[PDB]
Image (tube, rainbow over all chains, first blue to last red; front, side, top):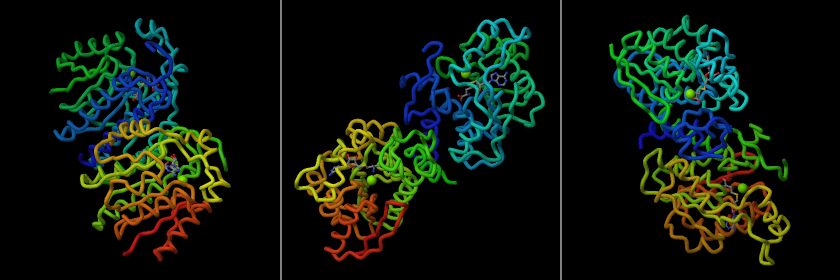
Length: 248
Length: 248
Ligand SMILES: Nc1ncnc2c1ncn2[C@@H]1O[C@H](CSCC[C@H](N)C(=O)O)[C@@H](O)[C@H]1O
Ligand SMILES: Nc1ncnc2c1ncn2[C@@H]1O[C@H](CSCC[C@H](N)C(=O)O)[C@@H](O)[C@H]1O
Ligand SMILES: [Mg+2]
Ligand SMILES: [Mg+2]
C-alpha cells in the first residue's frame, strides 16, 4: 500500500529471488520449491540470501520495532553469505531515511572455518566446513559489495568486518546494537558473537538465532543464557530460526 | 529517496534483472553485458522484459507525466513477451495508489505470426516468426500471469488481450489511453495498433514505438503519421526506441 511497504516487500522477494525462482544446490535435507524458499529451507544457486521469507519478515519486524520504539544502535549480522539479509537491512534504513545507524556485515568471507582441536565436539561432529563448495558458501568481500551496489545500497552506512568472529568481534568498532543477527550455524560462531557482541545489544534490542534447530548452536545459546541469567522469551520464527527481545 | 523512488527503481532493476544478470540468448547481433541490458539490446534467458533500462525509464516518464498532468486513460502495451514492462507499469500505478486505471496486456501469447501472402513485403523479408524458438518468444498467457503474481501485482487492474492485434484491437474493451506502447517489431503489428488503438490515446498521452530502427516499423509509423497529419516531435530514447506526445 505505502511506497515503503512496496519497496520492502519487493526487496524481500528480490533478495530471496521469489521473482525468478532460482534452483537450489543439492545438500543436507535436499529445483525451486515455493514452501522451501518461504521458510529458508533451501540453498539457492543464485539468490542473495538463504534465510527465506519468514526470517526476512522477522528481520524487518526487529528493525522496524527498534526504530519505532527509539531503541538505539546499529544492526549487525554475523554470517552474511552473499549479503541479502544485510542488503535488505540497509534497505529498511534507506526506506525510512535513517542516516544515523549502520549495517555491519561480518564474515570470514571464506565460508566455514576448518575444524581445530579447540572446536566444541558438536562443531567437530558436523564439520560445516565440508559443505562450503557444495553450497557456494565462500563469498568474497568484493562479491558481497558488488551485490549491495546492484540494489543501489552500497554506501558509507554499510561497514564490513572481514575475519573470524573470535578475531573481529571483541574489538569491532560499533558502540551499540539494536539488532544482532547470528547466522554462524556452529557452537563456536554463536558463542563467539554472544560473548563479544551481545553486551552491546541495547535494552529493547533483538537477538536472532538463525539456526536454533542445529544442536551445537542451541547448546551455545543456553550455555550463554544460563551464564548471564537471561530469561527473555525465545520466540520461534519458522522451522529453525528464533529470536528474543532483550529487557534490562 | 522516498519509498516510491526506491520501489520503482528496484522494480526496474528487477524486471530487467540487473540484480542477478542472467545470460542472453544467442541471436541476431549477439553472456551478460551491462551496457546491453542498459539499452535493451540483448535477449534475456530469464529476465521478464527485453526492453532494457532506458526504455523502462521512458515508460516511467510517460506514465508519471500522465498522472501528474491529469491525462485520462489506461496504459496498453501491444507485445509484452514475459510481461516485464506491463508489470512495471502496473507497479507504477500501485506506487501512486491509483485504482481508476488499468494496464492492458496485449499479445498473441504465441510469439510472432507465421507469414501470409497478406503480409507487407518487409514483414515477409524478415520473417520474425523464425526467431521464436531461438529467443523463447512464445510465452503463454498463464506464464505471464504467474510473473505478475510473483511481484504481487496480478489483480483486477491488469486485463489481458490474447490474440493477434488485427483481431483483438478494433473491438478491445478500453475507452481511453494515456500511454500506448507499441512493441510488435513489424509493419503489421505497428499498423494494426496505430490504426485501431491510437485514436483512443487521450490528448496529452504518449505513443511509444519500441522498434523504430526496424525499417518495416518505421515505414508504418510514417505512413500512419502522414495519413493523419500528425506532426508531434519524434523523440529518441536509445538505439531503437522513440516516442511522441500527442497534442490535440
Ligand atoms: N567463526 C566464523 N567467523 C566469521 N564468519 C563465519 C564463521 N563461521 C561461519 N561464518 C560465515 O557465516 C556465513 C553462514 S550462512 C549466512 C547466511 C546469510 N545470513 C543469508 O542471509 O543468506 C558464511 O558466510 C560463513 O563464511
Ligand atoms: N501481430 C501480432 N499480434 C499480437 N501479438 C504479436 C504480434 N506480433 C508479435 N506479437 C508478440 O509481440 C511480442 C514482441 S516482443 C515484446 C517485448 C516486451 N515488450 C518486453 O518488455 O520485453 C512477442 O511477445 C509476440 O508474441
Ligand atoms: Mg543459518
Ligand atoms: Mg521490440
